[PDB]
Image (tube, rainbow, N blue to C red):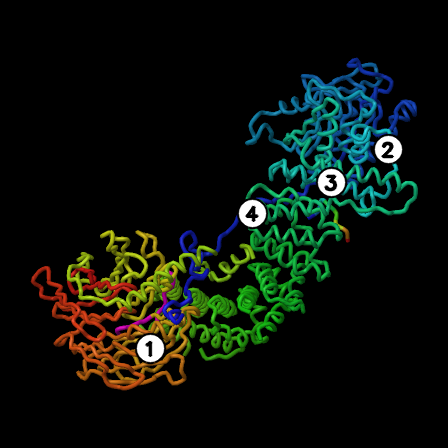
């Protein structure tokens, strides 16, 4: 579950 | 008007648990298993990168101005320093995409140097992918023999490195970039390296991916607006290159200071900075094109698998566009359809312009007065436009990959999530589409967001995902997403429909998943659920959650006992909804698994008893569950239950009754379950146990989104009815036309025993003495269908009725043992399913259906009249008749709900108001022979008066019970042997039948309207059971049938 980053 | 008593709005047994033609789903059948296609676990990594650079500086090869490379002027530095920096720059340029990988550089190399470079890279990244970037600008073009060009030590000759040898040095998991003229040559060669076959596509086999700059004949640009490094600067520095191209072409260039593009503020990461927000739009734009352009399989391989390949193929679509302008057609090996001038680059062009203007004033001062671009709002609005108009399987929505990018930023997260659920709601196909785009992990990560703004949407999204693919269990537990929904159960955030979803989502997380069982068990999910047990869908699902939580996991089974779950579940076994009760039986059933008493024996006895109460339930759905829970119990207590079967052929003798009861259940799927239970005991290894179905059917509710013609044919029949009610009453009905309108041969050997004229169509239903059913048409002279109501050996017909006459009739068939079977589509030539079948009376059964109240009254040679509410499928009441002899006849008033008439074996007559605390209203003798009341009914009207009391004696006694006990009017139809009576529903008319071959018709005041005499067809002299007489319910037609083999219809001219 990844490829594009999410802000946290 | 008052005639709405004649015209009841109650519909019954037309719910989803009673479904029809292309779904045996209803229950008995197991749930529809799926096979997913979005499954590539191998998130591939490019571990090694091999940058080769063949540019002899100030040495044009003999196939010949722009000469910028990696954004460096190689003539500014002198050749060796130039080439050092380009080497580094170009590493850094790639490095930004896959920073956790090793980059090795080779500047103007020998073939030996390229051999080792490649050999070491393969040895470095064993299974991991290896990138081979090649740049042959200062060397000759690739050959038709498939050759890269390199050097010799002295730089005197150009040496051709053949592609075959490269392909042997690197291997399977690898990707090549070719920034050179005539680049196709290399791919055409690569294609010819291996023996054709080994795939079902254009021409592939391995995992060799290839990106080439231009076609075979073509040459890279010379114009100074471009660098030499165009393809590489598209692929590797896309944003910088995309804007520099935008200036030099579109706006004409000299207005906008082009060197501001180098000095764009912020970084590529912050979507709140102008650089990163531009970078984010580009990713979003490019990814979107790829998704719409490609198929599922190829897209997922290039654009979703390897962070580097994803980036290289995204950035390739920019090359597709830029290179096209410079007389160049780039090609990848997985070939991909034409990308340039898609309707989405338009959106990029617009966002770039709005950016590039702003850049002028943001340099004047770091004001950070950076208005976010509308792009992300605008596209989400285009997704709403799709969701209303054309919202079908009418090609995908196109904005879907952009909604996913929005989930990465709080800026539009809520409205994206909202619109995503809106999209997910329209069916599994949409969930399949979402999960193809790659929604799963971002929506999964959001299960650590405390924002209560979101949660009601997140539960709805996770409901829909788990409704399709059960298998997400494993991830949800592994990240601790199970806690999210357990909160939501206990949350003060209202709405129990949202909580059923929460309970369902947990049911699926737990379902056959001991890691999920344990992790929910720790999280007190028993306690949470049992707290709520003190709305129906929510109750249904609270039980199914618990049922799954105990199932075969005995630590939870114990926790449930000492949390007194039996004490809180068992009261749902009485609930009006079968769906609740069946789910309640499931939960108690899964709590299972000489003279001894430990904690559990007390529970397991108290359980089975409370389940055995529900063995005789009026819903198959429930009985199916009770039989499964009995099978479970039976497995563990073979020892006892065999000894119980010995003496029959404490609580174990109760079970064996119920097994044989189930074995001879009407509904054959319940029957064949009871026969399974019997075989588990040894009357005629876990794998033999039948499996509960209630969970599986309920789950189908969610995988399904969360009319006018219904009322059309409803009012059709009501108009016809009202008109023909009046026409029955107000017509001066003349004498009977003895000329019949049929004498139909059933081929019933013993003959016809009961019949039933259809209101709104030209149909007769008849019944044999062994319950064969025909559907004869009288206007066509044709059969419509045949039957065998139940295959059991003991036959015997009691009643035919219609149910829901006002919208698609269902045929009720009462058997003399009190079994009641309701059929859909009986009028169709073969297709006719048993909707529901239960056993009233728990003998000579008599039955009556009262559409007004939804009640089915039933009794016979018993002390009690038993009442069934078919909306609930529940035995609502046992009224004692108070007679000490048999109920021979039973009529329910159509006008007055609850009220009931009953004729008796001793000639007696009784009213009941079944809704009263004392139900017997009055009890009157009328006619005085002490022979049985063959037939009775309420007078055609709107009062509690009664035709009634045709006795077998022969007298048809009329009476009004508001005023006096004795008879209003007597008619002596027959000297003995009254075999049947027919009273009309609205027309003032009746008829009676004799065992002396004879039929008679009377006005309601009692005038001989006509005699008929059924003659025998051979000299048996046995027309002694003129058993069926029955009027049409809206016209004056008379059907009639005997102990011969004919059903003749008459009228009144």
Q: Which residues are magenta?
A: B835-848
Tag 4 residue = B429
Mark 4, Cα crowd under 10 Å, few <14 / some 14-19 / many 20+, is few
Q: Does the residue at mark 3 contact the one at mark 2 (Cβ under 8 Å)?
A: no
* Label 3: element kind: helix
Number of numbered callouts drawn: 4
Q: Residue at x 40, y 53 (%)?
A: B21
Which corner quadrant of the image does residue B486 belong to? Answer: bottom right
In the image: residue B429, left or right of residue B121: left
Q: CA distance from mark 1 to mark 4?
A: 57 Å
Residue B312: percent from left, percent from top: 73, 35
Sequence-earlier tag: 3 or 2: 2
Chain to which mark 3 belongs: B
Report whether mark 1 lies on the same chain as mark 4.
yes
Which part of the image, by quadrant, shows the N terminus of chain B? bottom left
Which part of the image, by quadrant, shows the C terminus of chain B? bottom left
């Amino acid at each position: 579950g990844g490829l594009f980053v999410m802000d946290e | 008007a008052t005639s709405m008593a004649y015209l009841p709005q109650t519909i019954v047994l037309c719910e989803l648990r009673h479904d029809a033609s292309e779904a045996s789903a209803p229950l008995g059948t197991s749930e529809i298993v799926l096979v997913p296609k979005w499954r590539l676990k191998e998130r591939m990594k490019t571990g090694c990168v091999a940058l080769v650079l063949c540019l002899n500086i100030t040495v044009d090869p003999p196939d010949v101005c722009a000469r910028i490379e990696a954004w460096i002027d190689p003539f500014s530095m002198a050749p060796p320093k130039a080439l050092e920096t380009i080497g580094k720059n170009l590493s850094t340029q790639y490095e930004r995409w896959q920073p956790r990988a090793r980059y090795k550089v080779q500047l103007d190399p020998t073939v030996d140097e390229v051999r080792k470079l490649c050999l070491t890279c393969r040895k470095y990244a064993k299974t991991e992918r290896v990138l081979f970037h090649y740049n042959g600008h200062g060397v000759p073009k690739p050959t038709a023999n498939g050759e890269i060009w390199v050097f010799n030590k002295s730089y005197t000759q150009y040496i051709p490195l053949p592609i075959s040898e490269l392909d042997s040095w690197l291997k399977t998991p690898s990707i090549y970039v070719f920034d050179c003229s005539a680049a196709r040559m290399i791919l055409n060669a690569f294609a010819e390296l291996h023996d054709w076959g080994s795939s079902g596509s254009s021409g592939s086999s391995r995992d060799c991916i290839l990106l080439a700059a231009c076609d075979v004949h073509e040459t890279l640009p010379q114009s100074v607006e471009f660098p030499a490094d165009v393809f590489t600067s598209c692929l590797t520095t896309p944003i910088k290159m995309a804007l520099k191209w935008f200036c030099r072409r579109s706006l004409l260039k000299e207005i906008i200071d082009e060197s501001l593009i180098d000095r764009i503020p912020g970084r590529q990461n912050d979507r709140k900075t102008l650089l990163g927000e531009l970078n984010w739009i580009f990713t979003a734009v490019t990814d979107t094109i790829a998704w719409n352009v490609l198929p599922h399989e190829l897209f997922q391989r290039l654009f979703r698998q390897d962070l580097l390949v994803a980036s290289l193929f995204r950035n390739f679509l920019l090359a597709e566009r830029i290179m096209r302008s410079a007389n160049c057609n780039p090609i990848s090996h997985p070939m991909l359809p034409p990308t340039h001038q898609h309707h989405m680059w338009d959106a990029w062009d617009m966002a770039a312009e709005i950016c590039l203007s702003q850049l002028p004033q943001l340099v004047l001062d770091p004001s950070t007065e950076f208005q976010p671009s509308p792009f992300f709002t605008e596209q989400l609005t285009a997704f709403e436009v799709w969701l209303d108009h054309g919202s079908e399987h009418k090609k995908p929505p196109e904005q879907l990959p952009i909604v996913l990018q929005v989930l990465l930023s709080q800026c539009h997260r809520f409205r994206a999530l909202v619109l995503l659920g809106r999209f997910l709601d329209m069916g599994s196909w949409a969930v399949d589409l979402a999960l193809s785009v790659g929604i799963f992990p971002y929506v999964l990560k959001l299960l650590q967001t405390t924002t209560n703004e979101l949660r009601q949407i997140l539960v709805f999204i996770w409901t829909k995902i788990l409704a399709l693919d059960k298998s997400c269990q494993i991830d949800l537990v592994k990240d601790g997403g199970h806690t999210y929904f357990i909160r939501f159960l206990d949350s003060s955030g209202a709405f129990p429909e949202q909580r059923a979803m929460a309970a369902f989502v947990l049911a699926v997380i737990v379902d056959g998943h001991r890691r999920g069982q344990e992790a929910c068990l720790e999280a007190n999910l028993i306690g949470v659920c049992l707290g709520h047990l003190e709305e129906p869908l929510f109750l249904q699902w609270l039980c199914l959650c618990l049922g799954k939580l105990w199932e075969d996991f005995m630590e939870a089974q114990i926790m449930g006992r000492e949390a007194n779950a039996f004490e809180k579940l068992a009261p749902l076994l009485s609930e009006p909804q079968p769906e609740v009760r069946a789910a309640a039986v499931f939960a108690l059933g899964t709590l299972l698994d000489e003279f001894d008493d430990d904690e559990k024996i007390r529970a397991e006895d108290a359980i089975i008893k409370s389940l055995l109460d529900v063995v005789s339930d009026g819903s198959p759905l429930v009985r199916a569950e009770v039989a499964v829970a009995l099978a479970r119990f039976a497995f563990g207590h073979k020892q006892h239950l065999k000894l119980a079967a010995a003496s029959y052929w404490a609580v174990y003798s109760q079970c064996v009754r119920a097994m044989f009861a189930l074995a001879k259940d009407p509904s054959p799927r319940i029957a064949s379950l009871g026969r399974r239970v019997l075989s588990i005991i040894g009357i005629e290894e876990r794998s033999l146990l039948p499996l509960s179905t209630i969970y599986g059917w309920s789950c189908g509710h969610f995988s399904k989104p969360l009319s006018q013609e219904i009322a059309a044919k409803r009012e059709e029949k009501e108009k016809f009815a009202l008109e023909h009610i009046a026409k029955c009453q107000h017509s001066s009905i003349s004498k009977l036309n003895n000329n019949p309108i049929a004498n139909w041969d059933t081929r019933f050997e013993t003959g016809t025993k009961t019949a039933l004229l259809h209101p709104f169509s030209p149909i007769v239903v008849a019944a044999d003495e062994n319950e064969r059913i025909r559907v004869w048409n009288y206007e066509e002279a044709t059969l419509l269908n045949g039957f065998d109501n139940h295959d059991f050996p003991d036959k015997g017909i009691s009643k035919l009725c219609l149910i829901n006459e006002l919208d698609d009739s269902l045929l009720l068939v009462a058997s003399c043992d009190g079994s009641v079977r309701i059929w859909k589509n009986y009028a169709t030539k073969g297709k006719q399913k048993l909707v529901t079948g239960f056993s009233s009376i728990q003998l000579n059964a008599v039955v009556d259906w009262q559409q007004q109240s939804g009640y089915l009254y039933a009794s016979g040679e018993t002390s009690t009249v038993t009442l069934w509410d078919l909306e609930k499928e529940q035995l609502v009441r046992s009224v004692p008749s108070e007679s000490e002899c048999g109920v021979t006849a039973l009529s329910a008033s159509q006008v007055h709900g609850g009220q009931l008439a009953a004729g008796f074996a001793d000639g007696s007559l009784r009213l009941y108001d079944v809704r009263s605390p004392e139900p017997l209203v009055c009890a009157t003798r009328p006619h005085q022979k002490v022979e049985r009341v063959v037939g009775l009914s309420f007078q055609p009207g709107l009062d509690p008066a009664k035709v009634v009391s045709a006795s077998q004696a022969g007298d048809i006694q009329f009476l009004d019970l508001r005023t006096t006990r004795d008879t209003y009017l007597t008619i002596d139809a027959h000297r003995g042997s009254l075999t049947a009576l027919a009273v009309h529903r609205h027309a003032p008319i009746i008829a009676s039948g004799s065992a002396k071959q004879l039929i008679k018709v009377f006005s309601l005041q009692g005038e001989q309207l006509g005699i008929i005499r059924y003659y025998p067809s051979f000299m048996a002299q046995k027309i002694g059971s003129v058993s069926c007489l029955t009027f049409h319910p809206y016209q004056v037609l008379l059907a009639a049938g005997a102990a011969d083999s004919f059903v003749s219809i008459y009228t009144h001219d």
